[PDB]
Image (tube, rainbow, N blue to C red; front, side, top):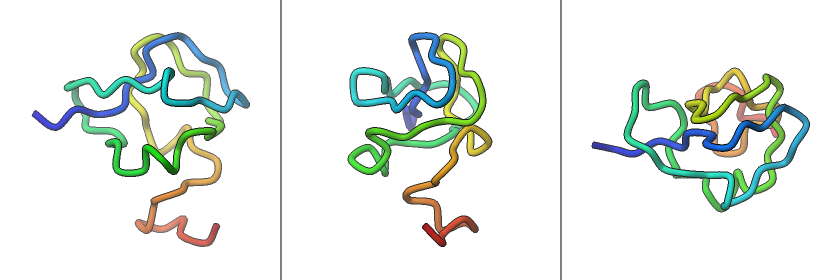
Length: 73
């Protein structure tokens, strides 16, 4: 039952999120976990995020802990 960060409050893009805007929920898919919690704090997404929106790799401009490919920044 690994909980995943699911945008609870409806937040658009270009809006740096923090801990209060990060709720670890157990829903599919797994989206982005909290491994980069202290690294995502202040991340701006590129796709509008509705309420309880599963964090996807498509709404992250500068991926912090993402060595899957975008490991340049």
